Image (cartoon, coloured by chain):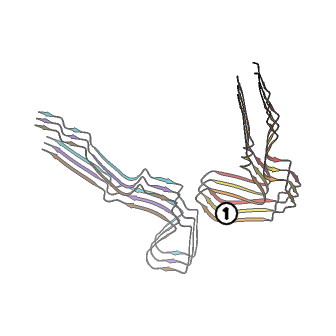
Chain colours: A brown, B purple, C cyan, D orange, E yellow, F red
Amino acid sequence: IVYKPVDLSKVTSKCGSLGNIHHKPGGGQVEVKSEKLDFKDRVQSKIGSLDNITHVPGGGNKKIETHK
Amino acid sequence: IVYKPVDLSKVTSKCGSLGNIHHKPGGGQVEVKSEKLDFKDRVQSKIGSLDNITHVPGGGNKKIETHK
Amino acid sequence: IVYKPVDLSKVTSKCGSLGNIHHKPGGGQVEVKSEKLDFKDRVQSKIGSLDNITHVPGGGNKKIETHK
Amino acid sequence: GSVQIVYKPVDLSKVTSKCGSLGNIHHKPGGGQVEVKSEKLDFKDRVQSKIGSLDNITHVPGGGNKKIETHKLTF
Amino acid sequence: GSVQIVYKPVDLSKVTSKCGSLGNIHHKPGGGQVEVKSEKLDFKDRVQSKIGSLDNITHVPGGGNKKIETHKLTF
Amino acid sequence: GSVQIVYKPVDLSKVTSKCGSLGNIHHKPGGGQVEVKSEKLDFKDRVQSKIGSLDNITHVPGGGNKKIETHKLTF
């Protein structure tokens, strides 16, 4: 009996934002004029901002191997 | 009995923001004029900001190997 | 009995922000003018800021190996 | 008999280039007032800028001369 | 039978380049007043800037002369 | 049988470059007043700047002369 299995395998996760090119992003002119505004509840505002947001809860790897 | 299994394998996680290019990001002009505004609850404001935000709760690797 | 299993394997996590290029980020002009604003609750404000934020709760590695 | 060869080519030629601004008269040229007011500008790439009232500009990459002579006598 | 060869080419020629600004007259040239007012400008890449009232500029990459003569007598 | 060869090429030719600003007259040239007012400027890359009232500029990378003669008498 000769027992010589060879494992050359790859398990790979590539998750999120990878290898992207963002070349000169952004608008020319943004102008906001506000007078006499009432807000009774929460305000979230973005004006001329650039946001790159990456969430990766995933991309996990599990490998199980058994030899008997 | 000859017992010589070979493991040359790879487990890899690449999770989040990897190898990206951000070349000259940002807007030209951003202008905000505010007069007589009332906010009764929480305010989150971004004006002309650049945000790169990466969250990685994931990308974990588990390897189990047993020989018997 | 000859018992000579070979392990040359790799377990790797690359988690968060890796190998990115950020070349000349930022807007041209940002201007904010505020008069008679009332805030009754918490204010978070970003004006012309650059933020790189990386959180990595993940990216852990577990390797279990048994020989019997 | 006998052989006589007389080779007396004469070159009196002119090759001339007159290139650019030559022999002009500019009598009391007046550039007006120049005002450049700039506010709130963004430039992402290379800028070349020239501001002025009166400009005389002469560029001459040309006007090159090439003369080739060959003289061959074989007997 | 004798042989006589007389090889007397004569070159009196001219090769001339006159390139750029030559023999011009500028009589009381006047550049006007120049005002450049700049506020709140952003430049991400190279800036080349030239400001002035009166400019005389001459650039001559050209006007090169090449003369080749070959003379060959073979008997 | 006699052979006579007389090899007397004559070169009196001229090769001439006159390149740039030559023989011009500038009579009372006046550069006007120059004002450059700058505030709140940002530059991320190389800046080349020139400011002045009156400029006379001559650049001559050209006007080179190359003369080749070859003479061969083979009997």
Q: Estimate the x, y position of residue D52 in percent, counting from the top left.
A: 76, 60
| Residue D74 vertical placement versus D44 (above, below) | above
Q: Position of residue D55 (x, y in %)?
A: 78, 58
Indicate the quadrant containing the C terminus of chain F: top left, top right, bottom left or bottom right. top right
* Residue density around tag 1, few if under 14, some if 14–19, many if 20 or more, within 10 Å: some
The residue sitting at 77% across, 54% down in the picture is F52
Residue at horizontal 82 percent and vertical 40 percent from the top:
D12
Residue E5 placement, left or right of D40: right
Is residue B17 highlighted in magenta? no
Q: Residue furthest top?
A: F1
Residue F13 sits in quarter? top right
The quarter of the image holding the N terminus of chain F is: top right
Q: Mark 1 points at which residue?
A: E39
Q: How far across and down, in percent of the image, does residue C60 sit?
A: 30, 51
Q: Give A61 or B5, whichever is nearer the viewer.
A: B5
Residue B56 sits in which quadrant?
bottom left
Q: What stretch is highlighted in magenta?
A: A26-32
Does residue D39 lie above or below E44 as drawn?
below
Tag 1: amino acid: Glu
Horizontal side, residue D17 vs residue B67: left or right: right
Q: In which quarter of the image is residue A7?
A: top left
Circle count: 1
